Amino acid sequence: PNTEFALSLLRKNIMTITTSKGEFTGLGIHDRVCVIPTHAQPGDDVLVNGQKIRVKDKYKLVDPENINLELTVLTLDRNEKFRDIRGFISEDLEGVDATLVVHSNNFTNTILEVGPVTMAGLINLSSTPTNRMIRYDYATKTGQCGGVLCATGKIFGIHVGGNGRQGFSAQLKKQYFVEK
Amino acid sequence: SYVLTQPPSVSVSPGQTASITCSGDKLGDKYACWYQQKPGQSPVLVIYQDSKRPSGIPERFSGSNSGNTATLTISGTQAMDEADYYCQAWDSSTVVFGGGTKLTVLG
Amino acid sequence: QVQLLQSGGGVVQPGRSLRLSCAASGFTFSSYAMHWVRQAPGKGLEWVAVISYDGSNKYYADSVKGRFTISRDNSKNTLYLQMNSLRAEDTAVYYCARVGKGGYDFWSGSGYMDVWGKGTTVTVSSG
């Protein structure tokens, strides 16, 4: 029933990004800047919705204690700029009924109602300690990495892992990006 | 054709745990849901998105999905649970029902 | 309050057409994909067809593709399955069902089915 924001994201900001590790959902933030899970390990080029695009720059986010945050910020060598969604990034997440918007592998155009979310903090994510993790009790799937955790007019984070009973997103913060 | 397999029948006495499975290639990478159908009635959703219970569905029903197999467990089976149970898988390209399992509750 | 009221069906001669219909009430019909699912006598549930929430996408099971059409009227909260070129193997109870909002693909209409109609019996008078 409440899909307008997710559909808007899918139409202007959410992509399928292919690396040598496979397909991931990716989120364009502003300009030519997008995010993908760090374990996607993007190379010098990626596929964006199937089209080969050179990676102008990339870097992995870590916190001030050098702990993995599991987000990699990519700058794409493409002319088109993303619709600016920096103003929707929200840390206002405790107890909100959130949605995952997925566009990769066998879950394209996919909207998941993951329920209330909370900050879990530090998690052992596939043997890498990872901070600023947001948790939901929902069954997630191998093909959904990169899914955008959001609510109406709010973007909370990016899905990066799970175990079939609980899923985890890397928190997105406005401070990760050029101020808008 | 993507095929989902279920055992034809399960039988338990009241209070026992009943376990009904459904299997298919990489089912654990798709979502599994479960429907209960009594004679002459429409199916009723009892488990969705692997493990969630709709409101009004008794807590004795639980679900899991991993590898190639989804499992519906009835912990403390009741006489009124006698019915056919159908698993259904979905992903972007998939909506498929398993062949069904007849659950008899007796003695 | 949430209701899928089905109508149509009956005995039909092979090769002919029959329309099944469903009137939806108690929810925002235009927001949901809808499926038809059928069950032959003493057999299991079989997916038949899907139509996406706005009617723009339609898919059919191999068994009915090229014969049946699915359609919807989001102003009159109605869903239709037009069954054409009927064959003995189409004999079944036909249910329509709503795709639940807990998790779904809004483009293909794939998902799980959280509300079901009572079912409509279609018997094709052929061996």
Image (cartoon, coloured by chain):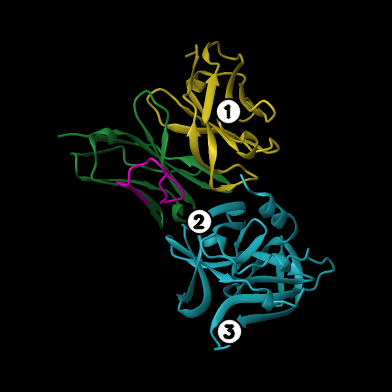
Task: Using the rendered view, name the quadrant where residue B46 is placed.
Answer: top left
In the rendered image, which residue does mark 2 sit on?
A: A115
**Taking B18 as reference, is C78 above or below it?**
above
* Disc 1 crowd, CA 10 A, few/some/many (<14, 14-19, 20+): many
Residue type for callout 3:
Asp
Number of the label disc, if any, that sits on residue A122: none
Number of the label disc, if any, that sits on residue C24: 1
* Chain B palette colour: green
Mark 1 belongs to chain? C
* Disc 2 crowd, CA 10 A, few/some/many (<14, 14-19, 20+): some
* Chain C palette colour: yellow
Q: What is the magenta range?
A: B47-63
Residue type for callout 1:
Ala
Q: Decide if residue A89 is in sight here.
A: yes
Q: Secondary structure at mark 1?
A: strand
Instruction: Looking at the picture, tell me which residue is in the foreground, B15 or C91.
Output: B15
Residue drawn 61% across the image and 16% down it: C17
In the rendered image, which residue does mark 3 sit on?
A: A63
Q: CA distance from mark 1 to mark 2?
A: 27 Å
Residue A35, image x and y in percent?
67, 71
Mark 2 belongs to chain? A
Dot in front, 3 or 2 = 2
Mark 3 belongs to chain? A
Residue A22, image x and y in percent?
60, 66
Q: Secondary structure at mark 2?
A: strand
Instruction: Looking at the picture, tell me which residue is in the foreground, C76 or C38.
Output: C76
**Taking C92 as reference, is A144 above or below it?**
below
Q: Magenta span has B50?
A: yes
**Taking B84 as reference, is A1 above or below it?**
below
Q: Are marks 3 and 2 on the same chain?
A: yes
Residue reaching furthest right? Answer: A79
